[PDB]
Image 1 (cartoon, rainbow over the protein chains, first blue to last red):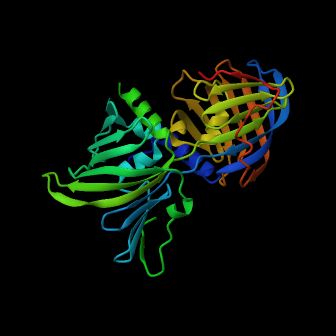
Image 2 (spheres, one colour):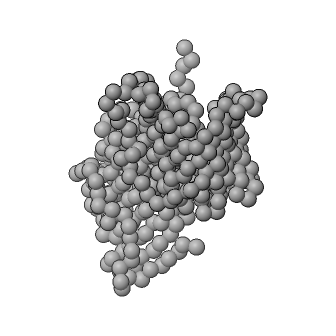
Image 3 (cartoon, chains in turn brown, orange):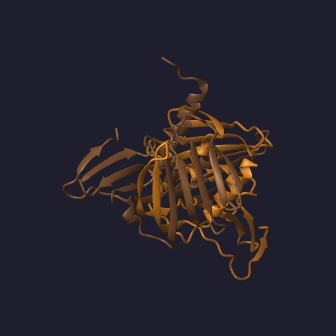
Length: 193
Length: 185
């Protein structure tokens, strides 16, 4: 019913272009180049080559107090409850909740520019520009070295979640523990249509 | 004032690319009801940056790690380093390599099958125009670019060999006996 307007047609095009390119995370190509000064006269020709490695997605893994987990490979968000042996898969794009963890882990200008952000020293307070009720509020404390010390989040139904972080070990961890395969026996609700 | 805050936040966060933290969490109603409490663990691996390496017709090379753009002319034994931020030109290669939504959302974009034509929203930019042909599988077949001076560069690509590329390629250290002009302030 609501027609496809120019702004959406452009968004759909950006999105398809992106999904195509998402399929190749690295490649090598030979090319032929041809330059033109402005008028049309052939300024230059030649052969060359190009290597590209695209960014990886962000990854995260959180263990709740109840010992159930949330795992993200950047596409899927997996939720797993080892006590009841139940697992839920959902595309991250359609995921709901856990936005602080997504913001924390992605650290992208473009996610940050969706908020009004005041800064007092190491403390930052973020109010959403688009007040649709995704996150009513988000607060975070980050050292100069980038260590996150604490943060809190207000959901749209005024549900507040606060976190105080300790024992912050930097240094890498193996990508295999950010990819989740339901263990034998676990009921899977795969909501990825 | 909001945009300095966003930047500094990001820049603090850029210093760390992975971490493990233990935490204590507390959850609340609108009222203030102590719905939850306990300890838990968080692991994060941040995105790494894009990388590209390009050999020009004249055999000079452009290498990018996401922060620095190195330009090296082995014939005259001269290399230039410049922050990628401060860089001018080579926008097509940055876009191809980054493949970020937010970079694509800076252009009005029309599609016809595999062909896409892009014109910048923010008309004060590097690129007057950018054209690219991408297959369903993500192979880039050709593209072309018009700079602000009406100059036009076209590329026709072949031999697209996907699969891992040695990360030798994307880190550049000036060779001994090459004169470096480090423009990074």
